[PDB]
Image (cartoon, rainbow over all chains, first blue to last red; front, side, top):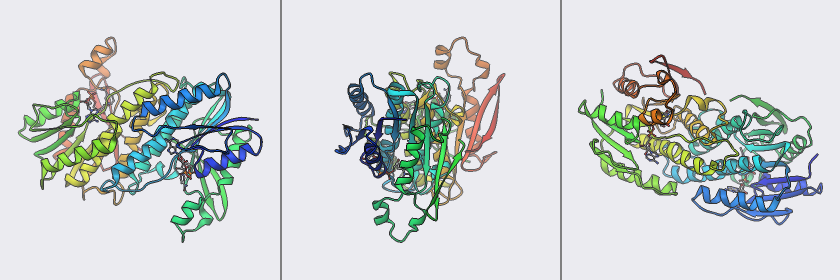
Length: 236
Length: 236
Ligand SMILES: NC(=O)c1ccc[n+]([C@@H]2O[C@H](COP(=O)([O-])OP(=O)(O)OC[C@H]3O[C@@H](n4cnc5c(N)ncnc54)[C@H](O)[C@@H]3O)[C@@H](O)[C@H]2O)c1
Ligand SMILES: NC(=O)c1ccc[n+]([C@@H]2O[C@H](COP(=O)([O-])OP(=O)(O)OC[C@H]3O[C@@H](n4cnc5c(N)ncnc54)[C@H](O)[C@@H]3O)[C@@H](O)[C@H]2O)c1
């Protein structure tokens, strides 16, 4: 029960799969990323800038003009990426900068967009990390970025957060996704423990059409063992 | 047991009290803030910029030149500030931008500085928020900022985070501090539930000189009831 979806990070591995999948069902899908998705119904290009407010104002304004008075069924915030490094790393700063822009910036704008354009009873999905439920000594930036997302998910389920009535804010907490990039970069790893993209797509679909949707403010761990994926709630 | 301290946010309410207090004991104290602290032994001025890596590289380089081969007993990261707003707020973006720069940026550089300049058995203090242990619907940015700090504290206590041997990473989680600004801005509030600055200063002093120091990765709630402050551990 949905025909209007926004995919934030629409050109990423997951995001791309979503656009394709929803377009195949004849849903109207807009992709919001640093580059265009010609497969989407519409594309919003995020401006590359160090200025958060400049980027945010730009996306908000453009989505505003694109939607008009139309509300969407869901906003899938699937933007992110990974970078490692401990506190001593020479690349700490560069990596932190990137991690913040990919996960914190996107999560924040998404949240704002949800308050303005999500239908009542609609869905917002955020991208967290199972690893970020604890200290992440070998990946400072990433852990911090994802931790903040987790926290934000809590805020949105609270009274007077600005979320539309009956809408839900849900964070997905994966370990590793099965992507060609992951495959090339971790060639001798056990792919049988990586989550297929299709599994998430099918899950999102369920959540949208009212099937098995968890409460707002839920942190859902996505863990794959021997090619079988399971969903397990985690508490903040 | 200390004579060398760095205060990050050295010109803030708390930070200022620290510099004064440690200088009074004849300790060498450097203040790192957006403005100079003429009361400190030394002052490092953070460059105002939207570029995280530009700001970070600048502080790191300058602290490096200032310290040389000298290690410090402690780094008190007391930088922050507060801004409110739900997800629907028109000022969300502006407020988020500020919250991130004051708490996330500072916490991150501080952490990096600790790995390079903290003595073994030294201390790093971070500034969190009791409120950020849950969803903060009325203060998105703040909650996110402080949540990330909490998470980072966890990372630094982990194996191979880059922290010097025996040093500790401790986050302080206040409710409200007794500041003249708070007083002017919340005039009919119960000041008897606000934490005196001196209490934190005395606490920091204890932590530095080895008295009653909690484990690394500790989240210490600071709660004042009827002018009596108490320290209570919280778990991530
Ligand atoms: N792949 C994994 O192993 C793994 C493990 C845990 C979590 N995750 C997460 O799940 C989500 C989906 O992962 P993925 O594998 O599809 O990621 P991806 O790297 O393949 O795709 C992320 C997308 O985000 C876009 N993006 C980055 N910053 C952006 C901004 N400011 N505005 C707009 N778009 C921006 C990128 O351009 C890219 O298209 C991400 O948050 C990712 O971190 C992935
Ligand atoms: N005052 C309260 O009621 C209250 C409640 C909870 C937490 N806290 C926190 O405890 C810590 C001490 O609080 P305070 O009352 O002394 O804060 P403050 O606002 O009075 O001082 C913070 C300082 O941080 C500096 N700063 C901000 N961004 C900076 C950057 N990028 N580089 C350097 N310096 C930067 C500011 O210039 C200011 O001097 C802060 O993290 C604050 O958020 C305060």
